[PDB]
Structures are given as structure tokens and as C-alpha cells.
Amino acid sequence: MLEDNSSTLPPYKNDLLYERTFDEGLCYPWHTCEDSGGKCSFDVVDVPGQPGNKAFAVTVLDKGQNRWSVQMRHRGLTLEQGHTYRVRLKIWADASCKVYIKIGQMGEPYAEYWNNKWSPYTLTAGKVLEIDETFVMDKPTDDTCEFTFHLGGELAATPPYTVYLDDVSLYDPEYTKPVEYILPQPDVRVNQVGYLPEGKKVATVVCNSTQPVKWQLKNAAGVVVLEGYTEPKGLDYVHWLDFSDFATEGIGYYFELPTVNSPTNYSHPFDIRKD
Ligand SMILES: OC[C@H]1O[C@@H](O[C@H]2[C@H](O)[C@@H](O)[C@H](O)O[C@@H]2CO)[C@H](O)[C@@H](O)[C@@H]1O
Ligand SMILES: O=C([O-])C(=O)[O-]
Ligand SMILES: [Mg+2]
Ligand SMILES: [Mg+2]
Ligand code: NI
Image (cartoon, rainbow, N blue to C red; front, side, top):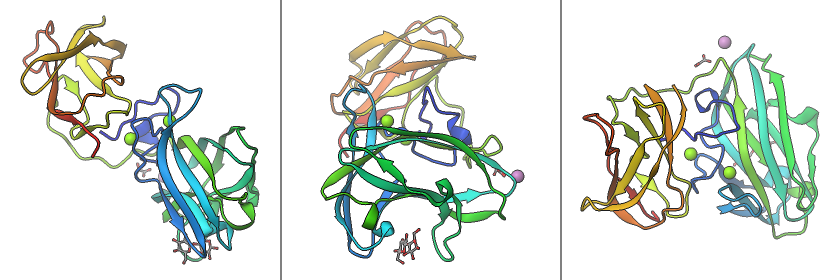
């Protein structure tokens, strides 16, 4: 499920970005680009001092010739004329360096629609830069935009070092992500392929009760391997089911809500595994 249930960002459905938190250990569609001598590598890693939180981590390896020689970006975005966008992120580095952040066209003529008025930011070693601001898309609608961070050339410290990105968001109240319609879902909603052992794992539960409800994780053989109570969130009634510490690989896990008087009181099957 693409929904991230971030407890501090605006609604996922109104975000132009598809990955914001990285807490499940995945970064796609975020990716690097290496150009004109630039080299880098990437991973998703835990953040020291922030338990449960993971960050997109791009290691600069060769600065290359230009600032765009090393990039981390998210493509496929449409900025709409007359709309107001809110830009939020946390970025830091384990070497003092600089970064040029922009939202613009991915190809020629490379129009830039937000770019901190053409100014790079400075990332002092270990010090977090947090951005939270708005801009108006007053140019005509463009469907070739990317949210990108240029790290190369003159912006770069002496490699190697790593730049981290987290809770990155592009919010427009008048935008709703494209949708597929889905069949009525069972009461427990999971990621239908699954989770990495080390990733955050929060399922969504809908049920009649306003109060917490008993849940059991069973393996494929139907044996209970973990139990808890849900955490009620709001309106039937939406609850969260956090099983992040469970890390045991297997195929065909599923939940059941044993006390819930519902013929759909389970989840679909899913896997925990490294793939
Ligand atoms: O074509 C090489 C490379 O271009 C990258 O875009 C750069 C471009 O090279 C540069 O002329 C312009 O001023 O900056 C942009 C980036 O904002 C592009 O990002 C790569 O995908 C492409 O392979
Ligand atoms: O903003 C829009 O037009 C939309 O939701 O596609
Ligand atoms: Mg995600
Ligand atoms: Mg995170
Ligand atoms: Ni509009």
C-alpha cells in the first residue's frame, strides 16, 4: 500500500510525492542520477537518535564537473498553474557541504518553479536543515517536473560522505493522487506483497469498536506468532496495528481479529522477506 500513515506530514493522498518517510526501508520512486563525472551510491538507513525512523541516504563518491553531476530526485510531477504548493523536508550530511534544491522541468529548457530564489543551502556536518514553506505555480501547467537535489561540482565536500533525506513532502490541497478502484477490502489492511524484516509495519484496521481491539498475527499454518491490541485513530472506526519489531521472515502470514463479529475479520496474506 502506498499510503504511509505519517503522523506529522499532511495527507498522503494530497502529496505529489509517492515516498516521503522511507520508514519501511524502500525509497522508490526517489533515485540518484550521475552525470558529467559524478558518482554516488544510495541506501535507506536508520537514523541515530530517531528510533523507528529511516532516511534516504546518498553517498557522494565523486563530485564530478557540475552541480547536477550528482543528484537525488523524484520525477513524474505536475505543477498546476494557479496552485499553491507546500514544501517540507529534513536534510543533513555527515560532512559540511552544500545542496541546491529545486522543483522544475526535468528536460530543456529546465524551467525552475521553486529553488530558494536560486540559492544553494549549506549543510553543516550533523546539522539538520528543515524546510517548510509555500510557493505559487504561476507558470502554465507542466507535467515534466522533478523535485531534485543537486550535490555535485562546487557544492560538494571532499568525498566520500553521505547526505540524508527524510519526511519529504509536496502538498497541494487541490491535488489528489491518481487512483485505482479496489474491491471491498477485509477488516485488516496490509501491504499486499509485504514487508522487509527491518521495516516499519503498520496495518490499518476498520471495525465497529471505538476502543482497542485484540489482534493476532498467524503464520500460513494458522499458528499465532504475535498478538496485540490496536490503537484507535478516528472515524466504521479506523485503527492502526503496529507490528514493526516483528522481523521473522515467512510467506503467507495473515491477521485475525478474534473478538470482532465480522465475517471479514482478517487480512489478506502477506510476506516478510528481504526481496
Ligand atoms: O543530459 C545530461 C543530463 O542532464 C541532466 O540535466 C541537467 C543538464 O545536464 C544541465 O544542462 C541543466 O542545466 O541542469 C539539468 C538538471 O537540472 C539530467 O538531469 C539528466 O537526467 C541527463 O542525463
Ligand atoms: O489537481 C488536480 O487537477 C487533480 O486532482 O488531478
Ligand atoms: Mg512508502
Ligand atoms: Mg523516515
Ligand atoms: Ni486547478
